Image (cartoon, rainbow, N blue to C red):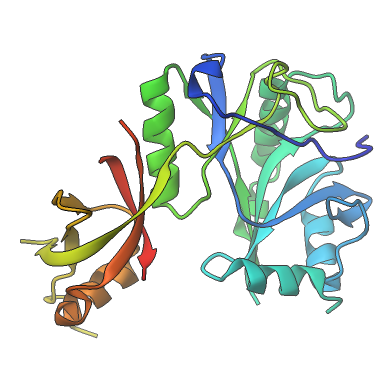
Length: 264
């Protein structure tokens, strides 16, 4: 049973991380727990009845996760989930089952096994159930590479958990290291100067952008991650249009691991 969701403490100093740790991507979405029906973080039922019903039928009691409409904006997702009414996803990152004191790695194994018994749940038409199985990170270099990866996939940053952590009915402290949020990359802007192609209906011949070279206050470097296929094609088909455009990107200050965020 769950009395209130598990919340995270903020990781400010990366050197504070107890290393053998389990990481997942920081999702920008609607926190939802399965307890009789789908509940939000305030533990009031999910306003969108179809989402509520669908997920309650699909998920086992004690499920914890995030609802989100894949390529939509946060404000779109918010109104779809939070309005008392399209395809959507549910990143399932925790499963209590019974005993909240059961270690985090173990609850994850419960989720994994449940899926093994019920594979078809990953096959729903409208609802995409995405099991958020953690990555074992061993050092700081691995943590930062992970944030770069995660940011390149469009996530906010990273969520850190100790393997033996319990499901706390409240916010974790930094010392507990049960659940921590990390956004170690810095936001910066750069002007686009040139582009480099990727492959050196029937439109399959056409090439797309592989990387963009940017200025960033005198220091030139390329950004080859952070864009989806759509972006790579658009940037390349109309490259003459983005030259001189300012792009938002992230990187780790001592640029290392640069990642494209957006235009303007």
